Amino acid sequence: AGLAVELKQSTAQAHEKAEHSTFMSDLLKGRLGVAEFTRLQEQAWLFYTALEQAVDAVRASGFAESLLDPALNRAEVLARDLDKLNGSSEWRSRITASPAVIDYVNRLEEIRDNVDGPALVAHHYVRYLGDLSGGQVIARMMQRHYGVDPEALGFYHFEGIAKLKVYKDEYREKLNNLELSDEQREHLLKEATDAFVFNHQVFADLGKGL
Ligand code: COH
Ligand SMILES: [Cl-]
Image (tube, rainbow, N blue to C red):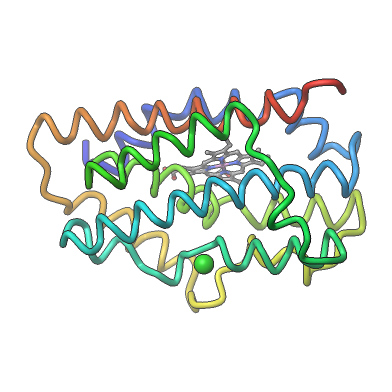
């Protein structure tokens, strides 16, 4: 199968397990609240910041350029959401990475410094295609259960993308058309599994003490 299908199939079980995370399932079903949603978004800001440094380095090396669309960048959008959610900008210098986020950020920094294009594409798929594909569902559950205002849910909307269904189709085709040696393809597929694990661990840390 093409790369896009192999990525979907190889991470499908991990995706189901993510939906059934105690923390995330509690958040989505309305058992938590805006503050816990804000805690999630703070951790996400930390890992998206690192992810986007790795994207920038890999794009600058000339690898996967058409996939690495800067319109996908989420860190600054997330920061605007968090300014609203937290009521001030102080969180920027106060939040601390959980142990899982330290691990995730460390890997993204390794990918940046090694300019590991195939690994970066795996992380790009796991975060951005998931955001493009499922973000609207998550945002709607925060609005409905907790009354989060849409202005604090900008992370879940891609302003620079006019035709979302078309964009997702074109993204998958770019994955299919990415030239990869056998070794690079195996490295990318393993990395996608690892990226799901890191994301699952973020939820586990957020759930501590609940
Ligand atoms: C409950 C909502 C929910 C959660 C918690 C969730 C948790 C996560 C998560 C957390 C660790 C990650 C890394 C992802 C990553 C992805 N999600 Co979701 N997703 C979610 C709702 C969706 C929806 C909706 C889609 C589109 C397909 C579908 O199953 O409806 C989705 C699709 C994806 C895709 C695209 C698959 C493909 O077409 O190849 C990726 C990647 N994801 N997702
Ligand atoms: Cl940004």
